Image (tube, grey):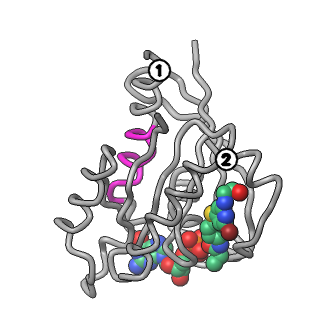
Amino acid sequence: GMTEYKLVVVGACGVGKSALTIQLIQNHFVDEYDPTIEDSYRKQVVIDGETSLLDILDTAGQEEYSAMRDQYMRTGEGFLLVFAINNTKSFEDIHHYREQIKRVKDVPMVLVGNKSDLPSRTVDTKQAQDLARSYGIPFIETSAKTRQGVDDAFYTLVREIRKHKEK
Ligand SMILES: Nc1nc2c(ncn2[C@@H]2O[C@H](COP(=O)(O)OP(=O)(O)O)[C@@H](O)[C@H]2O)c(=O)[nH]1
Ligand SMILES: *CCC(=O)Nc1ccc(Sc2cc(Br)nc(NCCO)c2)cc1
Ligand SMILES: [Mg+2]
């Protein structure tokens, strides 16, 4: 059989939410994608031997209330909290995005440090590991540019959802 999963990607403007989503649904790096386009995308993959259909909401546009975004998040099964490793403000914003999820939802989440390919790092991996431990969630490093860690981010979120569903 198969299993479907309703996923959401959040994080500051410009961290690579769309780039990560497009690496998952198209397998290449799309470096220019309208920052205002918020939509859900579907991709069938196989995770640990099971056919898995991932619906992914790539959040975008004005950071003002959107009822469709709110209703999708309220019924979302898992969330990626994305920051960019060369942007300290994006990392400092993670708590804000996690609070928004807690206000609308045990919630499966994965902390994602994107843009790992950039040498201009400002957030140490150890800093991010401390934050993910404080939340009780996994931390995964990614590069949407090289595809490093992309399947790890999404598939770890699916594995967290499976654990949650067993409770
Ligand atoms: N070097 C590098 N650039 C990235 C990566 N992910 C995204 N980008 C770039 O970061 C910018 C914002 O990406 P985008 O996907 O639009 O971010 P979003 O606003 O979170 O959807 C664009 O210029 C992308 O080309 C990555 O992993 N590495
Ligand atoms: C630069 C464009 C961009 O990335 N915009 C963007 C980032 C992240 C989100 S997620 C979000 C934002 C806001 Br104001 N509120 C919520 N609340 C939960 C759902 O109602 C989520 C959106 C846009
Ligand atoms: Mg985008």
Specify the amino acid type for callout 1. Answer: Glu
Magenta part of the chain: 148-157
Horizontally, is 108 left or right of 4 in the view?
left
Q: Residues within 10 Å of mark 1 (few under 14, many from 20)?
A: few
Mark 1: which secondary structure? strand
Q: Where is residue 144? Give x, y as percent.
A: 44, 65
> What is the distance, in whole Å, between disc 1 and disc 2 at their CAs?
25 Å
In the foreground, 166 or 51: 166
**Disc 1 versus disc 2: nearer the observer:** 2
Q: Quadrant of the N terminus?
A: top right
> In this orientation, does residue 59 appear?
no
Residue behind label 1 places its C-beta within 8 angstroms of ligand 1: no
Residue 50 got which mark? 1
Q: Is residue 153 magenta?
A: yes
Q: Residue drawn 44% across and 64% down?
A: 95
State the residue lying farthest toward the left. 126
Q: As shown in the figure, which amino acid type bears the numbered disc 2?
A: Met
- Which SS type dominates the magenta stretch? helix
Name the outermost residue toward the bottom.
120
Tell which of 82 and 116 is nearer to you: 82
Q: Is residue 133 above or below residue 115?
A: above
Task: Give residue 112's quadrant in the image.
Answer: bottom left
Q: Could you say which disc has been placed on residue 73 in the image?
A: 2
Q: Position of residue 84 (x, y in %)?
A: 40, 74
Q: Is mark 2 within 8 Å of ligand 2?
A: yes
Q: Which mark is residue 18?
A: none
- Residue 151 lies, with reference to residue 125, above or below; the image says above
Q: Position of residue 36 (x, y in %)?
A: 74, 75
Q: Residue at x 55, y 48 (%)?
A: 102
Q: Residue lying at the far front in this picture: please name it.
A: 103
